[PDB]
Image 1: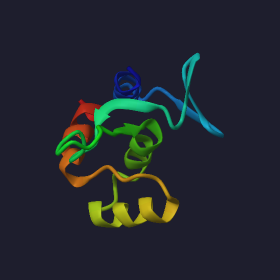
Image 2: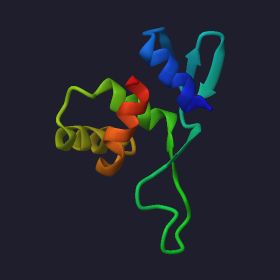
Image 3: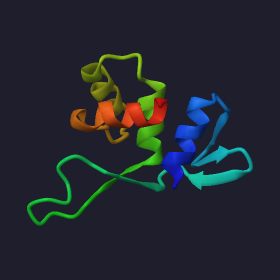
Length: 98
């Protein structure tokens, strides 16, 4: 699963290459909008479909982790990238950083 690959690359600081709409991990590649297996907070409940974070959304959080979460939310809105919702933030960053 691509989120486990992203964890591995992030923890060992191995280069991740973004090229147009593609993300390259070593000699492997995924579309940037590939769905991870991480269900978005609030979805999959009250009869509404599960939705999953895209790889792009997670990379954008990682690249902007220095911001306070509210300012990051504004940056995601401005860049038209889905936000990682606050209830998912600590767990996702914990998983990605080990």
